[PDB]
Image (cartoon, coloured by chain):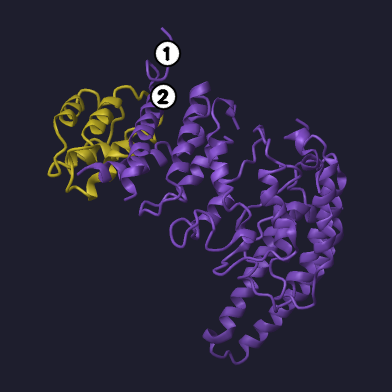
Chain colours: A yellow, B purple
Amino acid sequence: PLKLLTNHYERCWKYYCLPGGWGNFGAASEEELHLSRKLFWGIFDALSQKKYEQELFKLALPCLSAVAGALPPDYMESNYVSMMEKQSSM
Amino acid sequence: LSAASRPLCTGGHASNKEKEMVTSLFCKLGVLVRHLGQTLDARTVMKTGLDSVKSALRAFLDNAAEDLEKTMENLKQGQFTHTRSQPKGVTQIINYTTVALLPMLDKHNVYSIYNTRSSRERAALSLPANVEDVCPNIPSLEKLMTEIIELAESGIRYTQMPYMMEVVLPMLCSYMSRWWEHGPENHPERAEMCCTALNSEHMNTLKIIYNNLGIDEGFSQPIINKVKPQLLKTHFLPLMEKLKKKAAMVVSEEDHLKAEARGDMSEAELLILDEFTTLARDLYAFYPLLIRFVDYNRAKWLKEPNPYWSKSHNFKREEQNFVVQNEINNMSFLITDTKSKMSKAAISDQERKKMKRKGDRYSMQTSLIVAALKRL
């Protein structure tokens, strides 16, 4: 909760210094225990894009890491939804 | 540097890499379907491709000139490949977004994949004439099912503009156009939940002069000479106008099949021939007045017919009598209300549904006309 809610409280543009580590960890692995790491992107898919129709370039590389990591993860049958709709509304 | 799709353009990357990977992966694995992560990635890329961008028209709208054509062609080809199988992954509704991506028709000269899908659909194109165990896909349970009706209805729907080839209008399209028109009876087979689910698709060229010039055409298309379709497409209008009855519940599909080709939905020569917009539309508007107002015909048979100064007063007076019957019914229900579960609640539901559908058909264009006439 304190990672979920402190972001979506006040500010619009603060998510540039943080998610370099999230991209590094999306390159690292896709652990089903660490599904919250996917859920922050899963809520940022709608709530991060506040108003103003901004870039797609940085967020491609997490999607390509998920494409490369489509083969390993199995046993996380419920968690597949989070990696899907990031590029739809962006 | 030329900012191509795969080279530079990130807007083209999500389409290019996804469609190329799909056409490489499942086009190869389709032989593996018919008898660790192949199934998981298959069900992943299924809905990642069907809903890569929910705004399918917004994706390929103005993102790139030629990439939309190549990618819509590859997507519809991949849809035509695995259309025959009966797997668990449902995409009959998801095909509607891909179909809507087309009119919101490009240059199909680069490849004839649309012709491939059309020829596969030509296996059982004429639905009621060819309905048998040799039906589409030759299936008993494989592809012969309920989803194909909605697929033909919504997925085959190009309302923007017919800039396609349309070269087989005398042989391929005319086959399902004419075998349907072989008789007045639609003649659907068992499990006929709705025989009008083919489409509201038919128009004037979109026995006949073009097919009469089979060697000559097979480039004098039938759409060029509008008189030959205009003869025998409009000749059947008087046949349906003559066929009627006093009892309403007998003829259920009488209004539906005529209302599509009769009125102003036929854009081909609607402004050229005034009869298609004026007289056939007047007949197709007057026929429901005698058809639906009888209480014998139920709403479930003619529930959703989504599609004039003369018939306006007739509808108003007959609906005044119908609402007076509803009010007498309400006065009856107030005095010693019996068990509403048996026939009264369903009667009120049927009356409300009929009145709401009539009011909605008035609110399409006739409500503003009624306001203007009342002011006049």
The circle drawn on residue A10 is: none
**Residue located 49% across and 53% down the image:** B137
In the rendered image, residue B208, in percent from the top left (x then y), is placed at 80, 45
Question: Is A33 in front, or is B3?
Answer: B3
Give above or below for B262 relative to B286: above
Q: Secondary structure at mark 1?
A: loop
Residue at the spot of label 2: B11
Q: Are marks 1 and 2 on the same chain?
A: yes
Question: Which amino acid type corresponds to the residue marked 1 in the rendered image?
Answer: Ala
**Residue located 40% across and 19% down the image:** B9
Q: Residues within 10 Å of mark 1 (few under 14, many from 20)?
A: few
Question: Which amino acid type corresponds to the residue marked 2 in the rendered image?
Answer: Gly
The circle drawn on residue B3 is: 1
Subunit of label 1: B
The quarter in which the N terminus of chain B is drawn is top left
In the rendered image, residue A39, in percent from the top left (x then y), is placed at 23, 41
| Residue B324 falls in image quadrant | bottom right
Give above or below for B203 relative to A89: below
In the rendered image, residue B110, in percent from the top left (x then y), is placed at 55, 25
Question: Is B74 in front, or is A81?
Answer: B74
Left or right: B105, with B221 as reference point? left
Residue placed furthest toward the front: B215
Q: Residues within 10 Å of mark 2 (few under 14, many from 20)?
A: some
On the question of residue B221 being in view, the answer is no
Q: Secondary structure at mark 2?
A: helix
**Residue located 47% across and 30% down the image:** B71
Give above or below for B276 relative to B65: below
